[PDB]
Length: 144
Ligand SMILES: [Mg+2]
Image 1 (cartoon, rainbow, N blue to C red):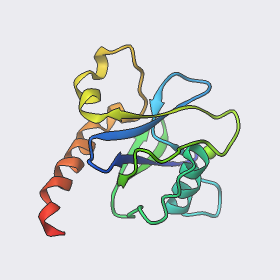
Image 2: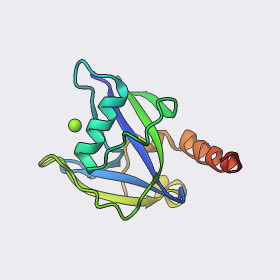
Image 3: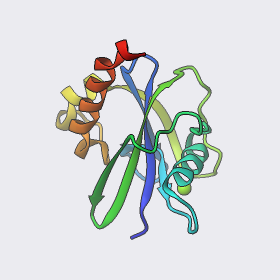
Image 4: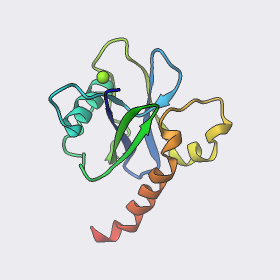
């Protein structure tokens, strides 16, 4: 049960989240991947997200901003990212792994969770701290 690191990526106005669908499942989830030995959490996340969506998180990632969950034996650590351009040309840099990359209206997801024909993984067990984090992001706007 090697740990997995990935990112929850929100757009400029914090209304949409970027999710990926693999080629062997119809579930939507965060871009992510297994720790490749002799590497820390941040480098793993940067490498894996770049492989899966072609975007380099180096200047965006904050080692203090993450959600951690143990799920079916595996440790997942999902870093929280805001301000990413919606019109960036996302595309995978590895073969046969990622089928689709799409922005989702985060409010709609929360409203239609276990009610749509759409399957999710990880994000459904993280809805609360995610929306708490977004709330917090608005509360601090005047601090900048
Ligand atoms: Mg990978």
